[PDB]
Amino acid sequence: GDQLYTTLKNLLAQIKSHPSAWPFMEPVKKSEAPDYYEVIRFPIDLKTMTERLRSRYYVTRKLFVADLQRVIANCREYNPPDSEYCRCASALEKFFYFKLKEG
Image: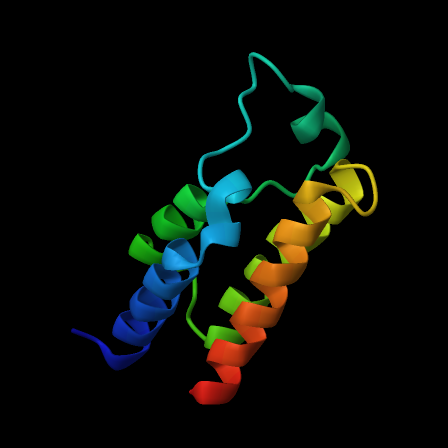
């Protein structure tokens, strides 16, 4: 497979493996929280990362970084501060940056 794609796929797999991914897996349920998309007019989630990756959105890892940071941002913006969601996003962030430092 293409080196970048494969790297990002592995990185994404690691991200999904990292428990803290849990809240951000699927898109926010429009039926329940439509307001997510109306406020956070910058949608992303890990399924969407997978879609974008498959769609070769991430022409450079920098864009993956940006979008993952977008998940973190979206979370912290939308959810009340210092929540389980914030903690999860923070664990995700640290884990992610750790993976980046590893490779």
